[PDB]
Amino acid sequence: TPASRYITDMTIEELSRDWFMLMPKQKVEGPLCIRIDQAIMDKNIMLKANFSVIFDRLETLILLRAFTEEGAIVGEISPLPSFPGHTIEDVKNAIGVLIGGLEYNDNTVRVSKTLQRFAWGS
Image (cartoon, rainbow, N blue to C red; front, side, top):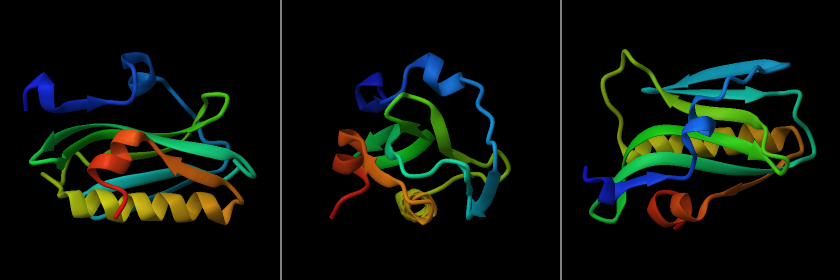
């Protein structure tokens, strides 16, 4: 994928930032791992991702992280090193799950423009 078809919602700093869940919960969703800090409640959350795109759709997810208005990371969808590969359907499965889990904790969740355009959104 040419840097032309690489979407980067997050900076290098954001991608690699260390973050700790106060009330960890994780889940393997097929070839993906979903992490949510359950201590996070009643907040507006924005999902941001870096992924490749082809034929007008997300092709391969590098990383997705959920940010609070203040810019703290409180959630994540990441590929499992072992499972080789994933589809956009895997990524969308994982996004619905992450959104559900965050809403369980009274959060309001939005996705980035690029996520909306390339994966999430009918």
